[PDB]
Amino acid sequence: MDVLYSLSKTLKDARDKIVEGTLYSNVSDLIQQFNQMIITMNGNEFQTGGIGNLPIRNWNFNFGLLGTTLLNLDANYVETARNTIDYFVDFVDNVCMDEMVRESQRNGIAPQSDSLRKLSAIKFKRINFDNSSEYIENWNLQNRRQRTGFTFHKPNIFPYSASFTLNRSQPAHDNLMGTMWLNAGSEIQVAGFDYSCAINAPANIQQFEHIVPLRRVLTTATITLLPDAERFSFPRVINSADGATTWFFNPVILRPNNVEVEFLLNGQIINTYQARFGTIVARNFDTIRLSFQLMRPPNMTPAVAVLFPNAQPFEHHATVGLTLRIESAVCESVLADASETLLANVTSVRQEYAIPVGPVFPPGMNWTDLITNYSPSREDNLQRVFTVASIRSMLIK
Amino acid sequence: MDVLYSLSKTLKDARDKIVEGTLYSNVSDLIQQFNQMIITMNGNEFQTGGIGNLPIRNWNFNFGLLGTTLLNLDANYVETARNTIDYFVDFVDNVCMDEMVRESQRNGIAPQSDSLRKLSAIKFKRINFDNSSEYIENWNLQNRRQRTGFTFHKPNIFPYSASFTLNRSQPAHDNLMGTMWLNAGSEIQVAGFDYSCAINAPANIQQFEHIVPLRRVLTTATITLLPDAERFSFPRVINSADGATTWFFNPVILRPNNVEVEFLLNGQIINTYQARFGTIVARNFDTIRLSFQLMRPPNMTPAVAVLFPNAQPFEHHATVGLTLRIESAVCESVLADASETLLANVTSVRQEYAIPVGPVFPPGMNWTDLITNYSPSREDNLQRVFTVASIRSMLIK
Amino acid sequence: MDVLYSLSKTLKDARDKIVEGTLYSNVSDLIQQFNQMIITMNGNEFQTGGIGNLPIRNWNFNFGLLGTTLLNLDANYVETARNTIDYFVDFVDNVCMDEMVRESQRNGIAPQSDSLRKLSAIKFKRINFDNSSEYIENWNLQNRRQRTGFTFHKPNIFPYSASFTLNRSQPAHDNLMGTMWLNAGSEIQVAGFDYSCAINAPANIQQFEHIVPLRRVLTTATITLLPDAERFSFPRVINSADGATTWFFNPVILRPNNVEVEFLLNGQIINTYQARFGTIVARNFDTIRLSFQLMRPPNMTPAVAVLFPNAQPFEHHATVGLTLRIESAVCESVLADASETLLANVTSVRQEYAIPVGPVFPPGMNWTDLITNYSPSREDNLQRVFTVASIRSMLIK
Amino acid sequence: MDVLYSLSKTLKDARDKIVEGTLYSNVSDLIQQFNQMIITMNGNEFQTGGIGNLPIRNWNFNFGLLGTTLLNLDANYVETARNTIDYFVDFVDNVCMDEMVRESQRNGIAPQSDSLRKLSAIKFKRINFDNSSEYIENWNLQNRRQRTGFTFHKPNIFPYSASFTLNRSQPAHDNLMGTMWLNAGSEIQVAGFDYSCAINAPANIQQFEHIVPLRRVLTTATITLLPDAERFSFPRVINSADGATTWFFNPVILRPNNVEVEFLLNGQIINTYQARFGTIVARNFDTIRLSFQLMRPPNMTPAVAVLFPNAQPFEHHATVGLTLRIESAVCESVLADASETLLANVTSVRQEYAIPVGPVFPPGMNWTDLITNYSPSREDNLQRVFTVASIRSMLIK
Amino acid sequence: NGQIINTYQARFGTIVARNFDTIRLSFQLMRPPNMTPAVAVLFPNAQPFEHHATVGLTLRIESAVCESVLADASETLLANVTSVRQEYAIPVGPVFPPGMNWTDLITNYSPSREDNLQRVFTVASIRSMLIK
Amino acid sequence: MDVLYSLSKTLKDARDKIVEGTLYSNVSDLIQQFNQMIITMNGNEFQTGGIGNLPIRNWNFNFGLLGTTLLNLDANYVETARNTIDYFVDFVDNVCMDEMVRESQRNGIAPQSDSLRKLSAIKFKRINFDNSS
Amino acid sequence: DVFEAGIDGKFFAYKVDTFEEIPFDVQKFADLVTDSPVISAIIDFKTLKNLNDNYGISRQQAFNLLRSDPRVLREFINQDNPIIRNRIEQLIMQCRL
Amino acid sequence: DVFEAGIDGKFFAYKVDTFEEIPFDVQKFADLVTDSPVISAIIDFKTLK
C-alpha cells in the first residue's frame, strides 16, 4: 500500500507535469521515476476480481520507455504517455477498490489483497517517489511508532443520541424537572428545565449536571461556547420513557448562572472554564462535564410575576441552556469530518458492488453505530480503509 | 489562461524563493525559467484596459538576464529581481483585470483580453512550468473532454427560495394545510403544517412531500439531517399570495414520523434513508426528496387534549419539519460556496470599474439570479472568470 | 526569524522526501542543503527553557555530513537521516515553545529569547533554502513594508456582545420600543421591536438604525443576509436596565421593510445594498450600518385584527430582524478563525507549563477580551506568536 | 530506548558471565563487546539528577580496556574490572531513576530523560548486545508494528467496584430483590438475592443478570468458574442506595440452574457456555455477561417449608452466587500483574523522591483510578516506565 | 525499626510498600448515625445482646523481594528438600526443627538457620536443574 | 516436531538479535544458522489448509542466503532479512495451526498433519538448533 | 530539624528538607518547646509523609505547610486532594460534644 | 504581581520594579484576596507612577 501511494502520486505527477513544451529537467525527476516503474512493472502478472462484484481482471504490462533526448515536450510524447498512464490509473483504482472491499479482525495493518500482498515483498521495494500528503505520511509514522496526528475541521465525535432524563415528575405531568441534551455531530446543546421555579429548593437554587464520554481523545481542541440552547426553545410534546402517554413543555428561557465547563482527562480537571463563552481551548481532554444551576431571580416585575407562581397550578416552565460546537482538532485516530470524501468514497465503492457486510464494520457503513462500538481492531481497519480512500481521492479527478 | 497561470505560479515560486544569502543550486532551474520568461517578453509592447473606469495602460519590457556567477545570493541581486517582479506582478494583475471584465454571449470558454489572446500564441506557449492549482488543473482537463469535479465546502447550489404553498386554505386561514421551506445556501428547512392536526383524512395521519431540483449534479456530498424545522417554529404573520390580507401562525412542533429521504438521479433512486437522522453520504444525485407524516397522538394527557379540540375551531396548529445541511460536496460544474475569495474579486472589479451591465450577468452579479437561471454557457463564463480570479489572487494578497 | 522557519521547512521537505530506494538525483539538492545546515550549525551551543514549567534543555551538535555517494537511496541513509531528524525535531520544538510564552510590552516583532536573538545574527545567514507559506510570506513582505494579507474562512471578528438599547421606556415595561443585537463570532443577529406597531409614530412608519464598527480594516468579505432573526423571535424574559427585575418580550414577526445595508470607510458610503437579500461582496470597509423599518400591514384578516389591539394593552409585540453572516474575508493582520487552528495551539502551549499571565495578552487568551483591545502592541505580539505557531505545526501536530 | 536494555543486560553479563578462571573463548565475545562499550561511553559529559530531590550529578568516563589475549582467567582481571563495573551499575541505576518519574501528556515513545535523550543518539548505536526478555521484546516489536502481548498470572484487570443493582424494593426494606457483585484484581464474585423466593414471579422462576465491561481486549485466557459464591453468603448490614439509613440482608444459598456465561467481543458473541463449570477458555473478547436463574423448588421438606411461605413476613432470604476468576491471560495493553515487582518499583520510585504530579498519571500510580480511565497515551507513558523498571529489575534491588 | 516508612489512610485496592518489617492496621467502628426499623433491632441501646457487630480487613501479599531466601509459592525448593529428607528418613539434626515444617522454622529466625537454608536451597535448585 | 521448535527458537532469536546496528560477532553464529536454514529449506514446497475453515495456503522458499559482508548491522540488511522472516513466521503460524487441530487414537507421539509428516524427511535434520525449553 | 508530640500516644522527629523521620529525643525537645514559638499542628505526620509520597512537594510548599499557611491549605482543599480532606474531616468528627 | 482595586471601579495590575500597566484577571484577584493579609492603599497606583 506504501507502494500503492507511490504509484498513485507518480501517476498524478505524470498527469500534471507531462505537457507540451516543458523543458526536460523540469520533468527529469519525473521521467527517471516513471520508467523505473516500467522496469519493475513489465512482465508482472496481476489478478483482481474474485470478491464482491469486482470483475476478474488479469493485468500484464509490456509498454516501453518514454523518450529522453527530446528537450521541450510535444503533443506526440504526451499522448503516447497518457496512453499507458490511463491504463496504470485504471489498474491502481481497481486494486484500491480491492483493498477497500474487505475487512479483517486479523490485524488490518497488513495488506488484505493478494495483489498487494505479492507486491509487498522485496521484488518491488524499488517503488517510491515521496510522501507529501497527510495520509501516507501518517501511515508511515504510525507503523514506526512516532508522533501521529490528523487535522480535522468539523468532525463527528459524538454519537448522535437525543434523549432526556427525569428527576421530578408524575403521571399528570404538571410538576417536572430534569434536563434534555443532544450531541449531534460536533454540536452539543443541553437544557435544564424546572416547573416549580425552585419554590421548594433550598434558597432558590437547582443543580444540573451533564456527562459525555468521547469515543477517542483530542488535544489542542478549539471549541465555541454559546449561552443558550438554540434547539430546545419552543413549546412541544414529548413521549414518556414508556411510550404510553405524552406530556407538554412550554419553555420560557432564563439566563443560566454559574455555568461550568470541565474538560477532564482520567479524572484530573485539565481545562477549566467559568462563564467564558466565545471560543475556548482544550489542550487535552477526552471527557466533557457541564455543570450549572437554575437560580430563581430575586426581584420581580408584573409580567415576570404572573409567569412563575408560588401556587401549584403552573403555566410556563423555566429553563437554563447551553450550547457547544467543536471547530477543529488534532487527533490520534481518523474520524469523519466536513472536509473529507473518504468516508464518501468508501461508501460509494462499497455500494456500487453490493458487498455483503463483514463481521467488523456496520451494515452500510452507518456512522453512529460504527462509532458506537469503536474498537482498536476497528480503528486499525478504518485507518487502513481511509488510507485506501485517500489513495483513490488523490487520483479520481 | 494556462500561460497566465504558469506566469503567476512561477512569480509566486520565485518571490517566495528569491531571497539573499541562500544557495543558487536550489533555484537554478527556476532561474533559467525566469530567463526564458525575460527573453520571451523583451522587445514586445502590450496594451491593457480600454473599458470601464480602467485607464488604458501600455507596458514595455526591458530587463537584463539574471546573474549566475554567485554561490550565495546577495542583497543587490535579489533587489534587482524584486524590482523586476514588481513590474511583472503589475502586468499580471492588469491582464487578469482585463480578462475578468470582458465577456460575450458566444464562445465563453476562450480568452477575452487582447493581452491574454496574444499570450495564447505558440511562441508564448513555451512559458510553462506546471499546473498545481485545482482550478487551472480542472480547466486543462475540461479543455481535453474528461470528467472533472470541484470539492466545495457549503456550496451555494440552492437558489434562495422562501415560498409557501397551501393545500387547504380558507378566507380566515384557520383550516390551513400547507408547507413552507427556506432554501438558502446549503440550508434546507422544510415544514409541513396542518391546523386540522390529523383529524380529517384516513389513517389519522397527514402526508407531506417536498422536492428540490438542482440545475447540476453533485458528487461525494456529506449531509446532516436534523429532525426539526428551526425557522418555521415561532409565531408569525405572513402575507397572502394575492396580498389581499395576511394570516397568523402559532405553531406547535411534533416529532416527525416515518421520514423518507431520497437522493435521486434523473428521478431514479440512488440513496434512500429512512428512520435515520445524522450524517450520511451522497455519491451522486440531482434531486432531493423529503417525505414525512404528521401522526396525531392516539393517546394524550389533558393538556394535549385541549391543545387540539376535536371540533372545528382550531387554536394551535400542528407543524413538523426537517433540516438538511450539506457540509461539503463535489460537483461536475464550478459553483459558488462558503470559502471562495474569487466571486468577490470579480464582482468588486466590475463595480469598482463600473462596467455598464451587459447581457452576460445580472447587475451587481446577483448570485441568486445566476443560480436561478443556470445555463452551461454562463457557467463556462463563470469557470473562465474564476480561473482568472485564482490567477489574480496569487500575487496581491 | 526567517532562519527558524527555514530550518523547519527544509527538515519537513527532507522527512517527506527521504525514503528507501529513490534515485540519488531526486533529493540530491536536499542532500546538499542537509549537509550544508549541518556544517553551518556545528560548534554552536544552545540552551532553551528557563521559565514556567517548560524545562531547561541544552543542545549541542557534533553531527558530521551524510553524503555517502549512492545510486539508490539506502536504509543506512534512511536511519542516518531519521536520527538527525528526531534530534532537530525536538530542538525546533522546544525553541519555538520557549519563544512563545515570553513577551515584551514593546517591539512586538523582535526576538524575545537568547536563542532566537542568536539565530538573528549573520553567522547563521547561510541556510535559507526557501520560505513558502502564507504566514512566512506576510513575514517577508512586512520586512518588505508591503501590503500584508491573510485569507480566512469565518473570521470571528465580532467580540461576544449581547446588548439591548431602549428607544422608549416604561417602568412597567408595557410600551418599550427598541433594538437588540447579538454579535457572536462572525454573526450579527439584529432585531428591532415595538409594542404599538407605531400607532403614535408619524406616518405609520418606524425606523431603526444599527451601526457596528470593527477592530481593524476588513476587506473582500463574502456575506449572507437573511431577513428573519433566528434568535430574537423566542418568548423571552429579559432582565431590567437597572438589574432589579425582568420583563416579558413576547414576539411576533413581520417582514423587514426598506432594508438598507451599507459598508462605509472613514464615514463615507462606499458599498450600499437595498432590497438585496442573499449573498453579497464587501470590498473595503470599517463600519457596517443596517437600516430597517416597521411598516404596519396596510390591511388585515380577522387573525391580525385579533392580534393587534388598538386599545392600550399590547400583548403581541411586533418585531423585525436581520441576520448577517460573514463567510470569508481578507485582512491586513492576523485574525482568529475556525480554519487556522493557531489560537488553540498558543492557548494549549501557554496553559501546559503554567506561565504567569503574559504581561501583554489578557489572561487565558480569552478571545473576546483579546480582540476588544486589539492594539498595535497586541497586533505585533499575536503576529509573532501565530507565525511561530504555524511554524511549529509543520512538524508536530 | 533499547540502548538502555543493552546497557543493563551487558552489565548483568559483566557481573556474572565473568568469574575467576574461565577460558578466553567463552566470554571473548563479551570482552570485545565491553571494550567497545567502554570506548563508546567515554568522552561525553553527563549531568544526571536534579528532579524532585534526586541530586544533580556530574559524570565522565575514562578507564583502560580489558585483557584481549589470555589463557585462563585470574583474579587480577576481575579485580581490575569490578570497580568500573559497579560504577556503570550506579550510573545506569541513576538513568533508570531519572527516567522513571517523568511526565509527558502528548508523547511517550521517544526519550524524555536528559542523559537518556542524549544516549539514544545514533552515535552510540554500537551497543545493542541482545534483546531477549519479555518487555524489551514487546517494545522492539511494537516499533515494527506486529502482533504483540504479555502473558499474565493473576492479571489485575477488573477495576475494584462494590456496587449493587436493585430491581425490587420499597422504603420499608422487607422485600428486597436484586444483585450484589464485587470486583478486584483478577476475580469477580456475584450473587443475586430474592426475598420472595420467586413466589410471585411468572413460572416459578426468576432471573439475575450481570454485565462487566473491560477496558482493554484480552485473548486466550483461563477462567476458573466456580458456582458457589463465598463473599455474599452471610448476614450483612449494608447502607441504602442514596443514604439515610442502613438495611439488613440474611441470605441462604441454593444451587443455581440454567446458568449461561458469555464472552462477547465488540458486540459479537465469541464464547458461549451453558452450565459448564471448572476451567474454560477465552479467545477474543472484552465483555462478560452472566445470566442465571433461581427456581422455587417443586417440592419441599419441613424446614424448607417453614422457611419459604407465600406470606408477607419474610425472615430467611435466598441467594445464588457465582465466582469467575481470570487466572492467566495474554494481552496487548500492558497491565500491572502479581508476578513481578514492576508496579511496586514504580510506586516506590515515585514516593522516594517527591515527583511533581500532573494528570499524565493518577497521583501516586495507585492502580484503581489508572485502569478506570485507561488511556492509550497514559498507556504509552506506562509501557515506557515499565520497561525501564524491568530493566532495573535485572541489575539491582 | 520503629521509624515510619510508609503510611496510607483509607486506600482501597492495590498499594505498594517499598521496605517494611512490621505491619500495622488501625481501624475504627462507628455506629451508623441512624437505623431503619430492622436495623434498629440489631442494635438496642440496652444490655441484652443477641447479634454482635464487627469489621474485617484482608491483607494479601502477591509479590515481594527479600535479602533473605524464603519459601515461596512459585517454586519447588522446600518441597524437594523435604522430600529428600522423607525418602531417606533422616534423624533430625539440632539446627533443623523436626518435620521441617516451614512455620516453626520461621518463628524464631536466627542467622545460622538462614545460612544452612541458603546452602540447601542452592543445592536443591542445582538438583532440580537435572531432574526437570 | 523438534524441527519446528528449532525453527521457532531461531526465528525468535533472529527478531531478538538481528535488528539495526548490532555487531556482526554476537549474531555471527546465528547468521550461519540462518543461512543453513535457508539452504536446507531451499527448494521444497509446503501445503496447508483444506481442513475446517482453515484457508488453504501454499508455501515456496526462494529466499536467497544471507551474506557475510558486515561489521555492524545496517537497516538495509535489516529490511532484506525481515521481509524474509515475515514469510517464514507466517509459514510457521500456518504450520502450528494445521498441527494443533489434529487428532488421533492411541497414537500421540507421532506427527499428525501432512506438513509435519513431510517434515520428518531426511534432509531437514540439520534444523535442530537447540532444545533448551 | 522539627519534632512533634501529642496526647494521642505517639512522638515523631524529622527534617525539614525531606520528611524522612529522625529518631526522637526528649531533652532538647522540652527546652525548645518551653521557650521557642509553638505551632499548633493541624496536619499530622501521617498526612505530611503521605502528601510527600503520592503528591508533589515544593520546598516553598513545605515551609508553608509546616507553617500551617492558609494559602496552601485552602488550595489543597480546592484541588480535591483527598488525604488532607480526610484529615480535616477527622478533626471535624472530633468535635462531637 | 500586584493588584489594586477601588470602590468606584478603578482597577489596576502591575509589577514591582517598573510598575508597568498590566491587565486585570478577576480569577487571580479571587484566589488572592481571600486569605492573605490586605493592604490599605493610602497611596494609589497613579500617584505611585
Image (tube, coloured by chain):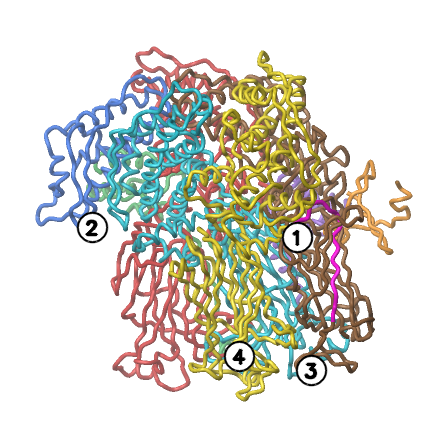
Chain colours: A cyan, B yellow, C brown, D red, E green, F blue, G purple, H orange
Q: What whole-number distance in Å separates the C-alpha atoms at marks 1 and 2?
A: 60 Å
Q: Which residues are magenta?
A: C280-295
Q: Is residue C289 magenta?
A: yes
**Secondary structure of residue under mark 2:** loop
**Secondary structure of residue under mark 3:** helix
Q: Is residue A133 magenta?
A: no
Q: Is residue G19 visible?
A: no
Residue, disc 1: C186
**Chain ID at mark 4:** B
**Chain ID at mark 1:** C
Q: Quadrant of residue A208?
A: bottom right
Which residue is nearer to you in this view: B227 or D341? B227
Which residue is nearer to you in this view: B316 or D338? B316
Badge number at residue B168 = 4
**Chain ID at mark 2:** F
Residue, disc 3: C306
The count of marks equals: 4
* Left or right of B245 in this view: B128: left
Looking at the picture, how far across and down is residue D292, in whole percent? Answer: 32, 69
Residue type at tag 4? Arg
* Left or right of D300 in this view: C207: right
